[PDB]
């Protein structure tokens, strides 16, 4: 009931009690673990609100105070009346920061309280959303000195007036099905690169074409918008030794800005809430270049290294994967763009873990996602036991808009 | 209830029905996941249903469920239990059990080989010296001059828990580790505590960086005794690198036979507390864990020095780079000497095939993602994007407290 977790590299033991607060469910049972599965009314709303407000006023050392009680009373009232309710800005911010704080899959959470919240709740149109998004992108980029941000569009009402960013990230590279058979650009984004044209995009049919924003406001049809290029900071990728690297014709964008998630605070459902921070190197280089179902350029890279690509036992894929990731980090640090290496980020996380166990009594963590996709066992998190559980406020997955939209 | 797993690299979807045959607990609940927790005297009361369960599986597998052979066997076992408070497995049953225990080992990426396991029945053993004999023949048989064969040796089951057979070594073959007065460690840091016990038990330690440890064996609950595996029986491979000639000079070598000996085999309620088993190495086990883990030989840095890497900023990925070269060297040294070894890409590929085959033919395949995924280059092996249900089946291999923590010293 008061669980412990052992780091095996260091024998350190943390005790977890925060999990007892856990409110939502995992997908696991006593009989089956699903830790490696990707995605396992006025009456429900009020308990949701109270729980949130209780933790909020507790966090400001005014638990049980007049303001607290009155606020709980005030919200309770508006709920009975309007069937929903609205969050004070302070609550909105506390909420946002805490959904990140509780994002069990996120290795970067040590930064969780330095989040810039943009209240875009007054928005009414796709054009408006576009204006708010450009503003976010510009702010977060900060000439390469990246800052974390989130922009929150009006909460769901009755599932009809839904605000949604159809892009999965604000900034992503187009991907096209070749008549040749293969795939040009980014394969992840193929179906999306279609929907854009299916909705009227004029694709430059290149490789690194920045996808257009497809914003949907108040449940209406979604509209296309193009991000001003001067707002899209990119880094041409080059190796600090292999000068044939730049020849490979590679660059990547500096701003990772996830847009398809649902943010939940005190029962309210912000279905558009694009947020961003900065890349861990391996997100672009292990994942965005070298996944089979992505840029898949490993073969060509090692080809250019004249490595024995005949048998797997030469570990050519590994050697190459390492150089590519060295290049990514090298180019970003060169162009004065924020990035963190996977050793540094995992180190920061262990500290953040220790910090949360100390000041908060625990920290939910999803080992399968926290461990970098390369060099796993030489990062400190590998040997770190982690408890996974779901807390509120949270970020949740949500169905792709094109599977839901009533046109 | 059906459950689906999806491979996100290939969109292949599989459907698990097997998880319904799962009894044992996971550690998990609906409000917490212990999926990354390393570790999450039995009466006639709870024995017979465990036995029936086993025998039922056993007779289904031989397509004789409900046969008179099956029913008499149940009866035979029943009566042997209520009379003797335990029972004995037939040879057929012991073999099936050991194989299935491996097959159910949800953390083992090597399971494709599960049906080809040589089972040595050492249930007639009575002394440590007898144990040394059995173990010696295991090692010789499994080693097969570098052409490794999977094998397990099974010592008598636990009776009253006061007469346990145990192998105190964690693996049959392992290098000593010595903590020095200055704080440094000579040999394998992973083995220091055991090395100490060994020394206290009268072992005369060479105190070299690569001393094969003695077997510390326990029979019928007696105090353990020391035995030196004859060196001609211990196959080793010196570690060199194919392009780096300075590598051999790091003075490295590893033993060829991985043979885990501290686990506990459970079959039909019976507990086999001494059941050393062996297969062959995946390269990363030696290369990534056995040299490069910060709590191991940690030649990561020296390899890095010799490569003249940029060890200043970690964002040079010098650690990553050295790690790769060390694993190249491990695989290369082994293949050159015709000692069986598998690389992580090969092993994971194999596993996916095995797993898919198991879903189709068995209705699932319990698998621990945290352990199946290799400790380097995770996402460029096919298991990384493979969803996996994890659950416990019997027969199984279980952890068990170190015997030095529980053992009652005769003297
Ligand atoms: C500032 C530096 C940050 C770093 C280095 C970082 C790092 C990461 C990494 C490496 C992942 C794994 C994702 C993958 O492999 O595809 C991840 C996931 C995640 N991040 Fe963070 N992040 C940062 C900022 C943020 C911010 C500002 C938020 C939101 C406020 C956030 C929320 C999340 C969430 C919810 C996930 C899980 C996504 C999922 O479940 O699929 N992160 N992060
Ligand atoms: C024949 C080639 C084999 C290969 C390549 C192989 C590979 C592996 C690897 C790489 C691990 C993870 C080890 C670690 O990182 O600590 C593992 C775990 C395991 N293996 Fe296999 N193995 C083989 C044979 C066997 C055999 C013969 C058995 C038993 C009869 C077995 C039973 C297990 C068990 C029970 C685990 C989980 C250990 C634990 O729970 O801590 N394996 N295997
Ligand atoms: C499995 N993938 C192919 C699909 C997938 C796509 C985006 C995903 O979002 C992850 C995510 C979320 C927030 C982040 C914030 C900062 C950062 N550097 N990476 C971040 C990464 C997760 C999964
Ligand atoms: C943290 N460690 C001390 C615990 C630990 C060490 C080795 C372990 O080995 C498991 C294991 C079992 C059987 C194997 C068979 C073959 C093989 N190549 N590796 C195998 C590896 C398990 C746990
Ligand atoms: C904390 C974590 O559960 C633990 O360190 C595990 C992680 N995965 C592993 N995977 C393998 N193959 N071997 C291990 O020893 C471990 N250790
Ligand atoms: C099968 C597994 O659940 C899936 O591939 C996960 C594994 N771990 C991951 N880890 C991170 N950081 N990001 C991911 O997308 C995934 N994918
Ligand atoms: Zn679980």
Image (cartoon, coloured by chain):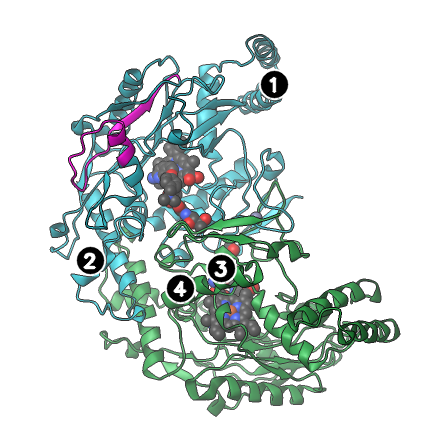
Chain colours: A cyan, B green
- Quadrant of the drawing holding the C terminus of chain B: bottom right
- Horizontal and vertical percent position of residue B63: 66, 71
The answer to whether B341 is drawn above or below residue A241 in the figure is below
For the residues labelled 4 and 3, the Cα–Cα distance comes to 15 Å
Q: Is mark 3 within 8 Å of ligand 5?
A: yes
Does the magenta stretch mainly form a helix, a strand or a loop?
A: loop
- Residue drawn 63% across the image and 65% down it: B398
The numbered mark 3 sits on a residue in which chain? Answer: B
Q: Is residue A346 left or right of residue A264?
A: left
For the residues labelled 2 and 3, the Cα–Cα distance comes to 29 Å
Q: Secondary structure at mark 1?
A: helix
Q: Residues within 10 Å of mark 4 (few under 14, many from 20)?
A: some
Q: Which residue in the structure is indicated by mark 4? A: B349
Q: Is residue A239 left or right of residue B103?
A: left
Query: Does residue B321 appear in this view?
Result: yes
Residue A301 — which label? 2
Q: Which residue in the structure is indicated by mark 3? A: B371
For the residues labelled 4 and 2, the Cα–Cα distance comes to 22 Å
Report if the CB atoms under discs 4 and 2 are less than 8 Å apart.
no
Q: Is residue A22 left or right of residue B324?
A: right
N-term-proximal mark, 4 vs 3:
4
Residue A46 — which label? 1
Residue A394 shown in magenta? no
The numbered mark 2 sits on a residue in which chain? Answer: A
Q: Is mark 2 within 8 Å of ligand 3?
A: no
Q: Secondary structure at mark 4?
A: helix
For the residues labelled 1 and 2, the Cα–Cα distance comes to 56 Å
């Amino acid at each position: 009931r008061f669980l412990k977790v052992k780091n095996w590299e260091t024998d350190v033991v943390l005790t977890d009690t925060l999990h007892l607060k856990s409110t939502l469910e995992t997908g696991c049972t006593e009989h089956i673990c699903m830790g490696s599965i990707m995605l396992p009314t006025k009456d429900q709303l009020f308990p949701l609100a109270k729980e949130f407000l209780d933790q909020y006023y507790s966090s400001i050392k005014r638990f049980g105070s007049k303001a607290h009680m009155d606020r709980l009373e005030e919200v309770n009232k508006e709920i009975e009346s309007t069937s929903t309710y609205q969050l004070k800005d302070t609550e909105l911010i506390y909420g946002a920061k805490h959904a990140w704080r509780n994002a069990s899959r996120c290795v970067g959470r040590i930064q969780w309280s330095k989040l810039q919240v943009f209240d875009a709740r007054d928005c009414t149109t796709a054009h408006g959303m576009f204006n708010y998004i450009c503003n976010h992108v510009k702010y977060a980029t900060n000439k390469g000195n990246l800052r974390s941000a989130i922009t929150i569009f009006p909460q769901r009402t009755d599932g009809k007036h839904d605000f949604r960013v159809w892009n999965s990230q604000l900034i992503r590279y187009a991907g096209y099905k070749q008549p040749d058979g293969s795939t040009l650009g980014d394969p992840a984004n193929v179906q999306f690169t279609e929907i854009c044209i299916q909705q009227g995009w004029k694709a430059p049919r290149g490789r690194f074409d920045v996808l257009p924003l497809l914003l949907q406001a108040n449940g209406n049809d979604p509209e296309l918008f193009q991000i001003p290029p001067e707002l899209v900071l990119e880094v041409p990728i080059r190796h600090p030794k292999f000068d044939w690297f730049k020849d490979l014709g590679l660059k990547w964008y500096g701003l990772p800005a996830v847009s398809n998630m649902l943010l939940e605070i005190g029962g309210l459902e912000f279905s558009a809430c694009p947020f961003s921070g900065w890349y861990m190197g391996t997100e672009i280089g292990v994942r965005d270049y070298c996944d089979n179902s992505r840029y898949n350029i490993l073969e060509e890279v090692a080809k250019k290294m004249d490595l024995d690509m005949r048998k797997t036992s030469s570990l050519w894929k590994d050697q190459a994967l390492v150089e590519i990731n060295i290049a990514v980090l090298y180019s970003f640090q060169s162009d004065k763009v924020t990035i963190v290496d996977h050793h540094s980020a995992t180190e920061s996380f262990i500290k953040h873990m220790e910090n949360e166990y100390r000041c908060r009594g625990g920290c939910p963590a999803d080992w399968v996602w926290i461990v970098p996709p390369m060099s796993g066992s030489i990062t400190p998190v590998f040997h770190q036991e982690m408890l996974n559980y779901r807390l509120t406020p949270s970020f949740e997955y949500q169905p792709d808009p094109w599977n839901t939209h009533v046109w």
